């Protein structure tokens, strides 16, 4: 049950995810998973980042889910569940702006 996950914010917009993530108290990797605004069957991983050039900022990554079962941001790296995907990216930055750290406070 992905709806049961505390990091799943459901039906919130890209702008709302940015409002939540752009809080100065959020360290790099603060994140949430929400519905994609324009891709049916897809989710979006929103993550906070911070650097001396941009300061506090937010990146969004589309998560695809196959009818064949797999979940992925890049098709070369798939998972059997969204929970497994989140756990993997909490340990590996790979192409993300930062590894996933803490769930975005509301
Ligand atoms: O449509 C989407 O899933 C989202 C998205 C994610 C990354 C890039 C473009 C669009 S959005 O919900 O932020 O627009």
Image: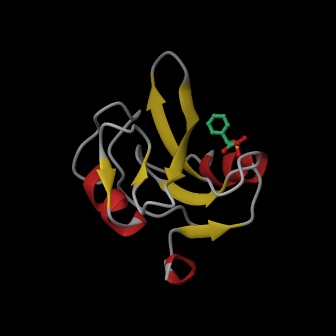
* Residue at x 26%, y 54% (from the top left corner): 88
The quadrant where ligand 1 appears is: top right
User: Residue 41, located in which quarter of the rendered image?
Assistant: bottom right
* Residue at x 62%, y 53% (from the top left corner): 42
Image spot of residue 91 (x, y percent): 22, 51
* Residue at x 38%, y 39% (from the top left corner): 75
Please say if 65 is above or below 84. above
Pick whichever, 2 or 39, lies toward us: 39
Image spot of residue 17 (x, y percent): 68, 52
User: Residue 54, located in which quarter of the rendered image?
Assistant: top right
Outermost residue, front side: 68
Query: In the image, 87: left or right of 57?
Result: left
Query: In the image, 43: left or right of 7?
Result: right
Pick whichever, 30 or 81, lies toward us: 81
Please say if 38 is above or below 84. above
* Residue at x 55%, y 36% (from the top left corner): 59
Image spot of residue 102 (x, y percent): 40, 61
Which corner quadrant holds the C terminus?
Answer: bottom right
Pick whichever, 50 or 82, lies toward us: 82
User: Residue 3, located in which quarter of the rendered image?
Assistant: bottom right
């Amino acid at each position: 049950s992905i709806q049961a996950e505390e990091w799943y914010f459901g039906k919130i917009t890209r702008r709302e995810s940015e409002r939540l993530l752009l809080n100065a108290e959020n360290p790099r990797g603060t994140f949430l998973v929400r519905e994609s605004e324009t891709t049916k069957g897809a989710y979006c991983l929103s993550v906070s980042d911070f650097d001396n050039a941009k300061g506090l900022n937010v990146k969004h990554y589309k998560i695809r889910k196959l009818d064949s079962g797999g979940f992925y941001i890049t098709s070369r790296t798939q998972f059997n569940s969204l929970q497994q995907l989140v756990a993997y990216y909490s340990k590996h930055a790979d192409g993300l702006c930062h590894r996933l750290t803490t769930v975005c406070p509301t």
